[PDB]
Amino acid sequence: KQPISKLTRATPGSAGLDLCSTSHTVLTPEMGPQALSTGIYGPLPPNTFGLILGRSSITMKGLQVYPGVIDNDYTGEIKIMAKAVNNIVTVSQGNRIAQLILLPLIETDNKV
Amino acid sequence: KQPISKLTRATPGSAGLDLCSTSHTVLTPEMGPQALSTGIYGPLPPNTFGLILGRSSITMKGLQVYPGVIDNDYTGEIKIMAKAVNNIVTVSQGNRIAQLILLPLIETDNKV
Amino acid sequence: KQPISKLTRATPGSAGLDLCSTSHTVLTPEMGPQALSTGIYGPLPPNTFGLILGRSSITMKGLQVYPGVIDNDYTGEIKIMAKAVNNIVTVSQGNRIAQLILLPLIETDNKV
Ligand SMILES: O=c1ccn([C@H]2C[C@H](O)[C@@H](COP(=O)(O)NP(=O)(O)OP(=O)(O)O)O2)c(=O)[nH]1
Ligand SMILES: O=c1ccn([C@H]2C[C@H](O)[C@@H](COP(=O)(O)NP(=O)(O)OP(=O)(O)O)O2)c(=O)[nH]1
Ligand SMILES: O=c1ccn([C@H]2C[C@H](O)[C@@H](COP(=O)(O)NP(=O)(O)OP(=O)(O)O)O2)c(=O)[nH]1
Ligand SMILES: [Mg+2]
Ligand SMILES: [Mg+2]
Ligand SMILES: [Mg+2]
């Protein structure tokens, strides 16, 4: 297992940490949502939660990433939920497919 | 009407407040986006805004929730904007279909 | 080029800055994702990043906006990544098609 801290940013001002697919995978529209492995695991830094979002270059090439919420205390593997929009999409091993954004986790009095 | 404060978190580290559908609804791909009732109303806590996002277990079962922005001062009913991706999806009353994330509302000098 | 500061909010409590299309464009489902011009450019205020999200009235009319991350130091044109869901969608010049949300950019020790 590899932690969040192993992820990298494209540039200092890049909002997201890049997430790569660990397998070669082919996706077609009729397959619907698929969960792609990353080999990267939660949990997140205290007081933060994560959002998985698409990279625009990948979205424009026809692979939609469904935004996903990563809970602060999640300790499982971060998977990318993805669907081919219109056409056959081929993802190669180590391709940068999504990005992880970290956001503040607001406290509320909501019952847990 | 029920306020945000009545919503619940799965767990202390869960980023989202769960949103349930108040009706039994069937969705097919050809129907396009549908607004599902929740019986839950704005407004939000001061200096925050909301984002409606899908639950991953639901996304992977073929129901896409379109991310929605809930404005701080919205006082209407929070509805879930949803679409069946590929197949017929059946939502039962009280099923947890989406989640509400609260985020800080940044001030800017943009004209209003 | 026009900066972010020229954008406007619907109302004081509106989380988003409105983004309008600079061209008349027709979209059909088979076309897949399209990048719509806005004539608005980065960069963003220090310590913030942007998220492009759909307006709910537009989503419910059948035009999906793919959430997009705007990096702090992006200096290019902000484009709206959009797809007609089920039907033919016609976007007119100056129509409000998306919104820009500003969020805090969290610092991490991730290698850049
Ligand atoms: O795209 C995603 C979304 C979620 N996740 C993981 C991280 C998060 O902590 C966990 C829970 O996600 P959701 O709350 O959105 N799913 P759900 O509500 O269906 O499951 P649970 O009831 O356990 O919260 O699933 C992913 O790995 N990828
Ligand atoms: O998924 C959603 C998205 C928005 N909303 C509500 C809450 C928000 O305050 C209100 C406005 O949403 P948008 O700003 O995204 N819609 P639009 O720009 O089309 O309407 P308005 O011009 O009034 O802001 O709609 C939902 O109930 N569900
Ligand atoms: O919907 C979008 C998404 C991104 N963008 C721009 C702003 C952002 O700074 C830039 C990078 O977006 P992504 O990081 O999501 N794309 P990608 O990872 O494919 O490119 P890069 O490797 O340069 O980061 O693209 C848009 O204009 N519209
Ligand atoms: Mg990127
Ligand atoms: Mg959940
Ligand atoms: Mg709006």
Image (cartoon, coloured by chain):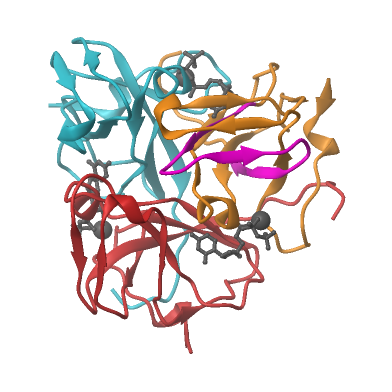
Chain colours: A cyan, B red, C orange
Asked if the magenta segment contains residue B28, the reply would be no
Residue drawn 20% across and 25% down? A28
Q: Quadrant of the C terminus of chain B?
A: bottom right
User: Main SS type for the magenta part?
Assistant: strand
Ligand 6 quadrant assignment: bottom right
Which residue is located at x 48 percent, y 72 percent? B78
Furthest residue in direction bottom, as rendered: B1
Q: Position of residue C61 (x, y in %)?
A: 54, 53
Q: Is residue A57 above or below residue B103?
A: above
Horizontal and vertical percent position of residue C49:
60, 34
Q: Is residue B47 left or right of residue A105?
A: right
Total label count? Answer: 0
| x 41%, y 15%: residue | C111
Residue C94 percent coordinates (x, y):
78, 39
Q: Nearer the viewer, residue A51 or B65?
A: B65
Left or right: C22 with respect to B27?
right
Residue nearest the viewer, comparing B44 with B89: B89
Front position in the image: B48 or B28 = B28
Above or below, comparing residue C60 to residue B20 in the picture: above
Decide if residue C54 is on the left or right side of residue B4: right
User: Vertically, is C3 above or below B36?
Assistant: above
Residue C79 location, x and y as percent?
63, 26
Of residues C5 and C77, the one drawn nearer to the viewer in this rendering: C77
- Magenta-drawn segment: C79-104
Does the magenta run of residues contain C95? yes
